[PDB]
Image 1: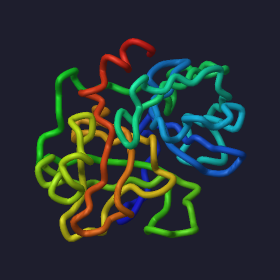
Image 2: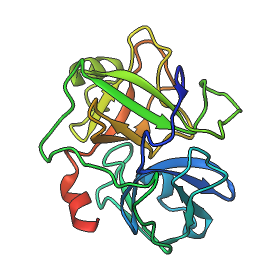
Image 3: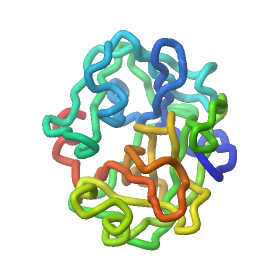
Image 4: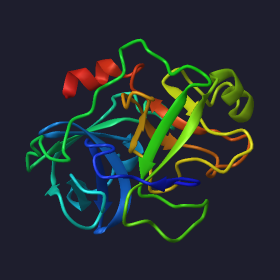
Length: 224
C-alpha cells in the first residue's frame, strides 16, 4: 500500500494475509469458515503447499488463526490479467467472532461508480519497487476511475468489464506488490474487488486495476 495509513483493529474483519515459502506474498478475503477469495495470479500454477493463510490479526506474522490449503480453484477462464480470481479452501476452519468476520460481497451485476470512494488494504510495498513490507496492515482510500479513463491509460483491450480501476490522477495512492488478492471495499465496507494488477504503483495516469466481485459473482457463489 502506497500513500496509506495504519489500519485499526477490526477495520477489515475478513482480511487475510497469504504468505508463500514463509515470506510475504498476497492478501485475501475470508468468505466463510473454510474459504478465502484471492487473486488467481497469487496461486495459479504454484505449489499449493507453499501457502499459509492468517486471519484475525493486523500482523501478517503473528496472532490470529492460521491455515494451510486443502484446494485451489482458479477462475476457469482466468486469462492473462483477466478473471483474476481464485477460491482457496482451508484445512483449518476459521470461525467468526472477535476480530474475525466474513466478507459482504457486492451485488451481482454491480460495477463500482466512477468517482466513488474505495478503500484498499494490505501488506505490500509502500512504494513501487520498494523492498520493505509492512508487518502491520495498511490501508488507503482512492476514488473509482471510469473504465473509459482506464482504457485511455491502458488500452481498450487491456481493460475488461471483469476489471475496474481506482486511483488518483496525480498518483501517490495505490495498492502495490504484495497487496494482490487483498480487499478493495466501498464506503460501506462491501467487498467490491480484489487487488489484481497495474503499470507500477501509484503512477499518475496509471490506475490500479481490480478484479470485479460484481462481475464474477457466478464464479464466487458457486464455489464459496
